[PDB]
Structures are given as C-alpha cells and as structure tokens.
Image (tube, rainbow over all chains, first blue to last red; front, top):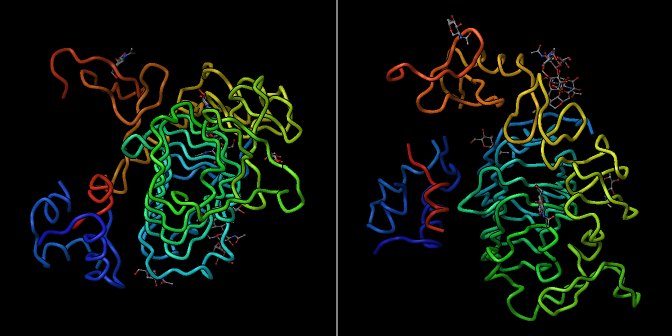
Length: 47
Length: 309
Length: 12
Ligand SMILES: *[C@@H]1O[C@H](CO[C@@H]2O[C@@H](C)[C@@H](O)[C@@H](O)[C@@H]2O)[C@@H](O[C@@H]2O[C@H](CO)[C@@H](O[C@@H]3O[C@H](CO)[C@@H](O)[C@H](O)[C@@H]3O)[C@H](O)[C@H]2NC(C)=O)[C@H](O)[C@H]1NC(C)=O
Ligand SMILES: *[C@@H]1O[C@H](CO[C@@H]2O[C@@H](C)[C@@H](O)[C@@H](O)[C@@H]2O)[C@@H](O[C@@H]2O[C@H](CO)[C@@H](O)[C@H](O)[C@H]2NC(C)=O)[C@H](O)[C@H]1NC(C)=O
Ligand SMILES: *[C@@H]1O[C@H](CO)[C@@H](O)[C@H](O)[C@H]1NC(C)=O
Ligand SMILES: *[C@@H]1O[C@H](CO)[C@@H](O)[C@H](O)[C@H]1NC(C)=O
Ligand SMILES: *[C@@H]1O[C@H](CO)[C@@H](O)[C@H](O)[C@H]1NC(C)=O
Ligand SMILES: *[C@@H]1O[C@H](CO)[C@@H](O)[C@H](O)[C@H]1NC(C)=O
C-alpha cells in the first residue's frame, strides 16, 4: 500500500492542499520503494 | 547585442504565481528555470502574463503540473537559446504532466546547445509532430516525447496558410517524411538555410555571424547577435575571453573587479547559495579545485604545499 | 520520474 508516481503526487496534493510544497534519498525512497505514514509524507508540505 | 534587462539567477517557482514576477526584468537566467506544482491556477491567470525580455537560459527549463497554462507562446515569446550547461537527468527541456498544455508555442527557440528534450504525459499536448527538433538539437536520438495527445490521430495540427491553401511554413524531411513545420496555428518554425549552420539568420534568411547562435538583427556582424555561440563581452560575441577578462559560467567575459565583488559579497550569511569566487585557469569560479587553496590578495588558486587547509 | 520526484519533493 505504497505510493508511486502519479499516486504519490495526488497524495501530496491532497495532504498539502493550500499550503503547497516546501523547497530550499528523497520521497521515492521513503514512500514509493517503502511505505511511509502520513506524518512522513506531510513533512513535504510548506508551513 | 547589449541586453536590455538583468542577468538573473536560477529560479524555482512553485504553488502560486506571485513569485513569477521576479522574472519581469531578466534577459538571461544564469541557472535553471523550474515552474511547477500550481494546482489552483486557471487560464485566466495567464491571459495577461508575459516575459518578452527572456532570451536565454544557461541551464535547463522544467515545467511540471502547472494547471490552466495552455501555451507558452505569451509566457516566453523570445526565448531563443537554452544552453544546457547543467541538465535535469540529461534534459535541457522538461515538459511533464502539464495537464492543460495544448501546444509548446516556443516559436523563437532556435538552439538547445547541450542536452535533450523530454515531453511526456501531457494529455492535451499537440503541435509536437510539427516541430523539426533536428534544427534545434544535434542529439535528437535522446529525445523522449511520448504519452501526449499527439500519440493518437486527434491532433490534426494545422499550420499557417492551410485554410488559404498555402504552405507559409518551411517544410523539412525527418527520416523520409516531408512535413511543414510550425509551433502554433499562427507561428511557423523558423528554419534557416543550410549555409548558416548553427549561427541563425535574420528575418530575411541572411546568415548571422559565425559567433552568433540562433538569431541576429543584421547578417555577418558579431555585435548584432541575439545570443552567442561561445562567449559574450559587452554587446559582442567572441570565441574566447581576451585579457584582461575571465571566462564566467561558460557564457560571459567578466573583469577581475566583478569576480572580486562576488567574492566579497559572500562574506557574512553563508545561506541563499553563495561562494567566495576565485580565479583559476582564466576562469572566475565558485571554488578552488581539490589540491588548491586560494591566495587571498588576488583571488588566485595556488596548489597546496602539503594538504590544503 | 522517480528522479523527478526526488529532486523536486523535499521535506524539512
Ligand atoms: C524590475 O524593474 C522595475 C523598474 O525599475 C528598473 O530597475 C531598477 C532596479 C532601476 O535599475 C531602474 O532604473 C529601472 O527602471 C523595478 O521597479 C522599481 O522598484 C523600485 C523598488 O525596488 C521602485 O522604487 C520605490 O519608489 C517608491 C516611491 O514610488 C519609494 O517609496 C521606494 O523607497 C522605492 O524607491 C521603483 O519606483 C520601481 N520602478 C518602476 C518603473 O516601477 C522592479 O523592482 C524590478 N523587479 C525586480 C524583481 O527586480
Ligand atoms: C568591471 O566590471 C564591473 C561590472 O561589470 C558590469 O556588468 C557587466 C555584465 C557589463 O555590462 C559591464 O559593462 C558592467 O560595467 C564594473 O563595475 C560596474 O560599472 C558600471 C558602470 O560601467 C556600474 O553601473 C556598476 O554599478 C559597477 N558595479 C559596481 C559594483 O560598482 C567595473 O567598473 C569594470 N571595470 C573595468 C575597469 O572594466
Ligand atoms: C502566494 O503564497 C504566499 C505563501 O503562502 C502568500 O503569502 C501569498 O498571499 C499568496 N498569494 C496568492 C495570490 O495566492
Ligand atoms: C546548437 O548550438 C551549438 C553551438 O554551440 C551547435 O554546436 C549545435 O550544433 C547547434 N544545433 C543546431 C541544430 O542548431
Ligand atoms: C530575430 O531577432 C530580431 C531582433 O530585432 C527580430 O526582429 C526577429 O524577428 C527575430 N527573428 C525571427 C524571424 O524570429
Ligand atoms: C601568494 O600569497 C602570498 C601572501 O599573500 C604572497 O606573498 C605571494 O606572492 C602570492 N603569490 C604570488 C604568485 O604572487
């Protein structure tokens, strides 16, 4: 029940919503090759 | 030609359009340009948005998940060269999951100096079969242009003149197939005579100088180039930087004082991506290579007697 | 694509 490619983006878009994504290994390793929980995934959202 | 606007650093524009206006005065982006992840934008947000001053990007252009953007023809009408100094996984141009893009429309793009094109998973994207990339890149065998509306026979790409029974656009041959080349219903792909090689030509088809790249305002004059093949020096295209100038970022000639000012701006606050620039082998560079340390009085890399500090 | 997501998506 891992998240890759399109599914991963859709999940980040739903979780982050209006906040957007943050900027300045990665998510594929944490969430696609492995399963990650919502608390990991949400760490990719901007404040 | 002396650039009307600024040289801006590489940018990464995300989430909303607010930060995009940071590009309003750039002629050259010395770095890459990434525009991505704009989920709530709509076509109305792009109806009055244009950056006509942008002529060149030294690295790569990446567009990913920008909603409501239907064409780039108004956004980057004058983008002529993407040098590909640095690339995104071997690509100088990346158009990925641009859900609403109907056409590229980069009708002034003449040369991609290094790297390839990846245009993938753009469900509305047409005006791809109409582009002869062989006029823009040497390495077209590394292009990855798949999973677009263009894959099937629903595009019907219509080039200027067709309605009037005319072929206004130049036609070129790609592996035995002869086809009229264009970017949109109203913009042809510019194609220069074979004699011009990679230098470009004026609107009238006259060859640019051998130091030009892609386009010029007057033929056979290195002060009339839109962009340079090698280096740029105070509104002139040159093969190499002469003394007392240094080669900078693989495209421009700068003086000692410029390199020095960069070095001494990078004093306090090591953040925001700064380096104390140095001189090494007639280049102004971010840091001394391994085995060298920087002689302080003249920014010059000297080899270290024993290990470097 | 995974190379794309790794490069663009960053936590912190
Ligand atoms: C893009 O360029 C515009 C236009 O100005 C140009 O760039 C300047 C840096 C100079 O080289 C100019 O010769 C050149 O025309 C920039 O807009 C300008 O922004 C400044 C503030 O940064 C404005 O000045 C302010 O004026 C008010 C009073 O009206 C004062 O209270 C402020 O203290 C301040 O002095 C200036 O009016 C404005 N100019 C115009 C024509 O709008 C713009 O900032 C620049 N964009 C970026 C992202 O750099
Ligand atoms: C050495 O170069 C610097 C900077 O070069 C400027 O930018 C280049 C891209 C190019 O357009 C040059 O012609 C520019 O001069 C010079 O310092 C700048 O000088 C201009 C006026 O000529 C001025 O507008 C800038 O603000 C100056 N910068 C600072 C920080 O003072 C410098 O004078 C040149 N020196 C020599 C001897 O050539
Ligand atoms: C753009 O996003 C920033 C950061 O959340 C915010 O400050 C600004 O108000 C936003 N503007 C618009 C028009 O959405
Ligand atoms: C693009 O420009 C470079 C100039 O450095 C040249 O080598 C290359 O062949 C050009 N390609 C085309 C097809 O214009
Ligand atoms: C090349 O640049 C000149 C700059 O004046 C512009 O007028 C011209 O139309 C460009 N070439 C073409 C035919 O796009
Ligand atoms: C290197 O630095 C030292 C001290 O600043 C100086 O004496 C020396 O002459 C410099 N090197 C050269 C080639 O001048």
